[PDB]
Length: 66
Image: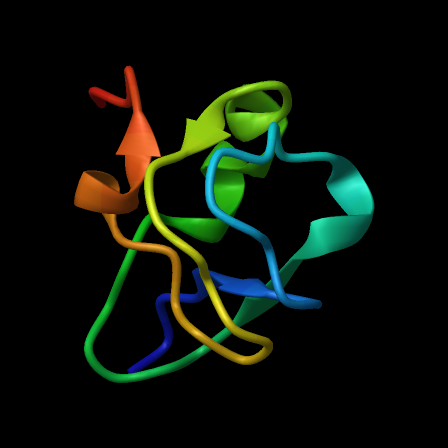
């Protein structure tokens, strides 16, 4: 487990466009969106509410493909 994922740094309400302060990098299980993609995620919209400390998964971000 050395791969870090994107984890919500605050509750992200449904349909919010992500900003940098909302995203942190953490080694969590299961693995979500790779923490290196945090750059690309800015301005993309989440399609559900992501509570504080939840791993951001590919299927929670609208338009995400990588």
